[PDB]
Every structure is written in C-alpha cells, then in structure tokens.
Image 1 (cartoon, each protein chain N blue to C red):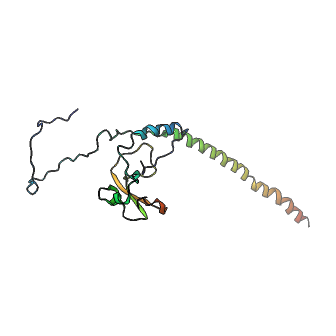
Image 2: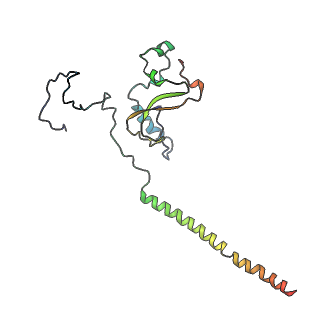
Amino acid sequence: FGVYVAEGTEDTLDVQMGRFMETWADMMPHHPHWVNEHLTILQFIAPSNPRLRFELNPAFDFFVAPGDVDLPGPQRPPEAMPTVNATLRIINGNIPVPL
Amino acid sequence: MDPYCPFDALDVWEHRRFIVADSRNFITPEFPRDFWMSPVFNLPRETAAEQVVVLQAQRTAAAAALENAAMQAAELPVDIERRLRPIERNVHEI
C-alpha cells in the first residue's frame, strides 16, 4: 500500500477512484506496520518491534517493496518477490514520532 | 485437480547432522492462498492497429504542413529573380 505508486487511467476520477476503493478493501492482507506509531519509545526499542532492523540511518527509511518493478507502474498491482527499498527522508519531522 | 501420486504420505523423522542424500524440499510460504491474487494481463487501452491509424493521421497532418512549407518556400528564388532583375536593368541604364 504505502510503497506502490500507480498510473492515471484517462478517467473521470470517480470510477477511477471507485475501483480503487474495492481494490483497497482487500489490498492490505494484514496490518501495515508503518501506521503503528502510537507506541512509546520504550515499546519501540523493545525487540518485539519488527521495524527495528528496518531503521539504520536517520536520513533514510528502510522498507519492503515490490522488486524489479519500475515506479510508477500499471495500476493493477504486479506480483513479484518482496525486496527492500529505501528513500530520502527529507523532512526531519518525518523521523518516526517515537524517535 | 490434485496432481497424481502413487504414495499418499508416510511418517518421517529427520535428523540434523546425518541427512544423507541431501534432498531439496519444496518450500511453501506462510501467507494464505486467499491473499495470492490470480493473474490478470492488463490489456492496453489502445491496440497496435489504432496506434497505426493515429500515427498515420499525424503523419498526414505533418506532411500537409511540410507541403505548405514547400509551397511557401519554393517561391523564394522567384522573389529573388523578380526583385533584382529590374534593379540590375536600372544599374545597366547608367
């Protein structure tokens, strides 16, 4: 969800938004962990935190994304091996709230 | 739908150090097959035939523009020979 970007489809933005709605209804098979920032620094530092080993440098974020896929790509989500991709965290305030 | 197999299943109790004739088990993932969506070939909005038609229409428009450029730019020698010859005659008049 939070790592894939799609294409415009020459549409009225209503049906185009509409189809995204139901594709979004099941797009997330589980909880995307990147929305869990209500936890305190104590809970974050705890080893049960999965995103710990995806935080190694303050300037960037580390995350899982589709591999061998050029962004943005076709709106229908291609299936491929999960991989690790990183981006620029330009805003210092974009650092996770517990940190 | 199930691929055929003469042997149903048996009871095997493997060890760590003495796996002899080290095989390659077929690994399986843990996410349910309900999350593994079926493949769909997203058909392009246009077809190569429509691409040919549109590109040929654009070529016709470009060729019409080039023909207009040709007819406007083919008269320049005519302008040259229409403008200088009276002046050349006038200079000869001296």
